[PDB]
Image 1: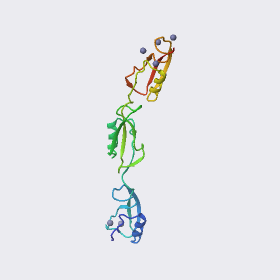
Image 2: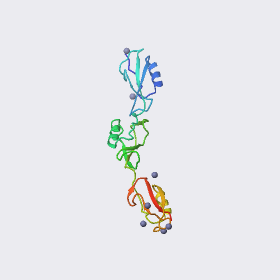
Image 3: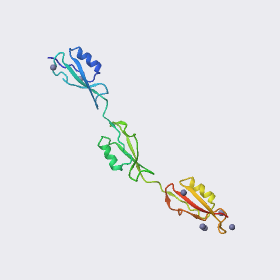
Image 4: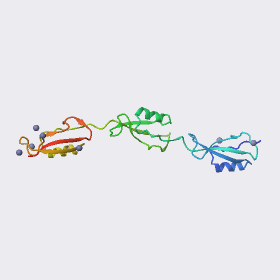
Length: 201
Ligand SMILES: [Zn+2]
Ligand SMILES: [Zn+2]
Ligand SMILES: [Zn+2]
Ligand SMILES: [Zn+2]
Ligand SMILES: [Zn+2]
Ligand SMILES: [Zn+2]
Ligand SMILES: [Zn+2]
């Protein structure tokens, strides 16, 4: 009894006018993600273009809600391969893993994600950068057994650690050098605490 006029790619507003102008009244506006059509253009009608409709009949449309979009999972504290799969199943597959140091997250675990958790994010051009954990950094402890503890504080601090010390008398180590040192220099560890015995005089 009549073509469904064509409204694919038009606003709802222009669509009613083409419908009304044809005796049809639109009615029933649903929405979708489209690859192909920009947000707000129409994608599909449901008698369907040029398919038969009766006059006074209504025709439903489905409008584009822009492109395919999703709520970012949280993956902080998951192990790397699990984290990657949470997002594979979700459509997030453009993922760059960047290894870094960390005082919370297990070696191998995700410390931190690019795009913030539970935001909605578009499977189009999501450059997902994930920060994997390496451990805490090992720094080196230069030995100071003999030598101005006064300087040595300054080394050690500037650089990782905090430094703790107490005083003994020695007539075998100049008032102020170092009688002993705690983490036996020349290993490497965290931002830990180096303890000193300093000749008191
Ligand atoms: Zn067309
Ligand atoms: Zn009908
Ligand atoms: Zn000594
Ligand atoms: Zn000296
Ligand atoms: Zn002692
Ligand atoms: Zn003395
Ligand atoms: Zn302490």
